Image 1 (cartoon, rainbow, N blue to C red):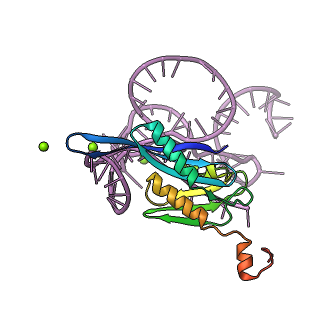
Image 2 (cartoon, chains in turn cyan, green):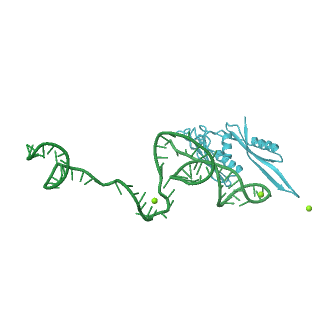
Image 3 (cartoon, helix red, strand yellow):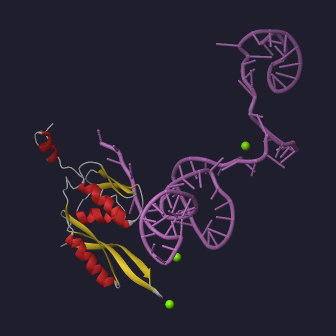
Length: 155
RNA sequence: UCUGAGAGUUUGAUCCUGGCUCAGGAUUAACGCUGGCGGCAUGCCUAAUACAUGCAAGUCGAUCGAAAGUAGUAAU
Ligand SMILES: [Mg+2]
Ligand SMILES: [Mg+2]
Ligand SMILES: [Mg+2]
């Protein structure tokens, strides 16, 4: 049940020897709401083929996401170009405090309660890149225990 | 035990810097349209401009002389 949702449908174009070639570009986010989510941007002369190619790319590039108590473990800032997205853990009940591309990414990934803020640009592809970078840079509290020879997150 | 949502807009199309605008609240508010009632609360932000009129700090005869009125033949 890999649900998908459309984030942006731009109308890009080039110029030829007389006239303009117009193609639709779609930014699709595919997620199973259990820990797998990817993104795919595709261009085609028509919306259906563009959506098909974007879904194919999103399913080709899937990333693994780990959740702690339905939320993100520690506060992080994802950077990608001029877009910086701040994610912050939330207690169970606040729900998704995200809006737009971040909200799409978080819901399709499976997180329940996240605090988010877009501190930079508002271009959906770069916001998605920053969000994915922030979630991917995350550290589990068992990898750090293995690294520092602590006792499975014990004090 | 706190705790933060964004979008539109420069280009044939894209990224960034960057300004403008909107989505939310609030008032000692005013205006247009309309208008049934009750519980609380507020009501010259301007001319510290000028004011008709009527009220807004008096009380004590158990401090004191006197005076007036009502009763009483008088004293009282
Ligand atoms: Mg020619
Ligand atoms: Mg234009
Ligand atoms: Mg005044």
